[PDB]
Every structure is written in C-alpha cells, then in structure tokens.
Amino acid sequence: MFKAVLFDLDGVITDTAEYHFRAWKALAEEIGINGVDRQFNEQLKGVSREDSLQKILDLADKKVSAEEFKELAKRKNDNYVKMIQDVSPADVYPGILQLLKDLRSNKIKIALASASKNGPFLLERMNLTGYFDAIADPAEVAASKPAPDIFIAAAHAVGVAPSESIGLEDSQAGIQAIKDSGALPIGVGRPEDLGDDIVIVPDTSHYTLEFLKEVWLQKQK
Ligand code: BEF
Ligand SMILES: [Mg+2]
C-alpha cells in the first residue's frame, strides 16, 4: 500500500481565491480603480502577482514606474496577509479533514506540496498542522510546477520515495509534476482541464482513504 499522501493546498485542502480577491479589491479601491469584482478575480486563478497587478492597472489603462509597480505588488501582499487572518477550519474542503484523520490513524505519512509561501500559516489557521509530517518549502525548489521538484521534496521530507506516494492536485501543471516525480496522481476537477489519462474525482468529498486504497491497488495491475 502507499506510504504517503502529498497534498496540494489551493483547490484541494482549501481555496485562497476569496482572500486574494479581497486583497486586490482593497488595493484597487485605495488607488481608485473600478472593476475588481469576483468575476475579474476568477481570471487571476494561477496568475502571478506581477501579471495580476498588470491586469488591474489595465482596467484603467494605467502605467506606473518600475518602483511604483514593485510597491503596489508589496501592498497587495500586505493586504493578502491581513485578509488570511480570517481563514478558519470552516475553509477546509469537504472530506479533507476525515481523510487526514484516517491517514494519520493508519500511520500513513502526510506532506504538503504547495506553491503557497503562506502554507504553514494557512494550515495553522485551519487547525490542520498536527496532521502534517512535513511541508515542502516552495522557496527551496529550483523549478515550480509542472517541474516535479516540490513533490520529490515532499516525499523525501517524510522518508519515502515518490513511487510510494499518492499526489492530490487540482491543476494540470500539478498533475504533470506528480507524474514526473514518480508518484500516483489523483486529480480533482474535470478531464478537460487535467488530462484524460489519470484518475479524477469531481470534488474532494470523493477523496476517502477507501477510494485512495482502491485506486492504488487498481493501478498496480
Ligand atoms: F497549493 Be497548490 F500549489 F495549488
Ligand atoms: Mg492547487
């Protein structure tokens, strides 16, 4: 049986989108730019801070200096840190808490393989820290997803080879990283987005220990 589960954070454990939305909306209002609504922020999913800021300035056809741009990006991050203080166990996605409990009670290792530089804090806010055996530090990988670096690091940090592990991901780049690490991917979402050659569940309530075990056994035949 698999010895570890490597968890992505955003789109698997929780969603940070509302908090990023709040942060951009606060910044936009401060500098007097209309149009930063929930719909607009949906289009920033997966998009870098710098590219996102440019999209906000584009709402007002606005140009700024390199220094001003840097300062605005910093201010957005300061806003985001404020907004995520309100993260709580209510933010945890369905099924995830029960899965973490079942993995730990069965002595299966649990690691975080997230791009979030606020991962440890977010886990603390959601009361999940005690379930995690390791957190792979994104600041430490030479290459981001789809590079497998972060999943390899997560597996190694809990004393396992990636080949002994399952990775859970909501993004196509994430699924690729899991595949190229040697771990077994189980995606959450749709094949149109993630690919047609992996096991996918429609939402996280399907991520049960029983299901993960069935998939593991089915995949080594
Ligand atoms: F937290 Be993962 F990188 F979406
Ligand atoms: Mg994700």
Image (tube, rainbow, N blue to C red):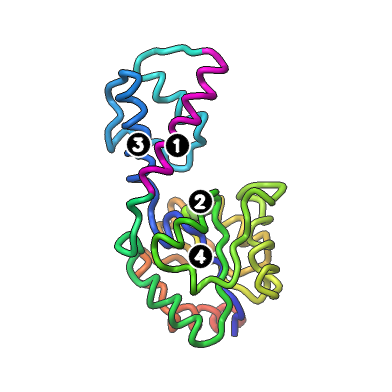
* Residue 211 located within the stretch drawn in magenta: no
> Front-most of 62 and 177?
62
* Residue 80 located within the stretch drawn in magenta: yes
Q: Any mark on residue 118, and which? A: 2
- Residue carrying label 4: 168
Mark 3 or 1, nearer chain start: 3
Measure the alpha-carbon separation of dots 2 and 4: 19 Å
> Front-most of 145 and 195?
145
Q: Tags 3 and 4 in contact by the CB under 8 Å rule?
A: no
Mark 2 or 3, nearer chain start: 3
**Residue occupying image coordinates x 39% and y 63%:** 126
Q: Secondary structure at mark 2?
A: loop
Quarter-of-image position of residue 98: bottom left
Measure the alpha-carbon separation of dots 4 and 1: 29 Å
Q: Quadrant of the N terminus?
A: bottom right
> Front-most of 46 and 200?
46
Mark 3 or 4, nearer chain start: 3
Res. 198 visible in picture: yes
Q: Secondary structure at mark 4?
A: strand
Q: Main secondary structure of the magenta part?
A: helix
Which-is-in-front pick, marks 3 and 4? 3
Amino acid beneath label 4: Leu
Amino acid beneath label 2: Asn
Which-is-in-front pick, marks 2 and 1? 1
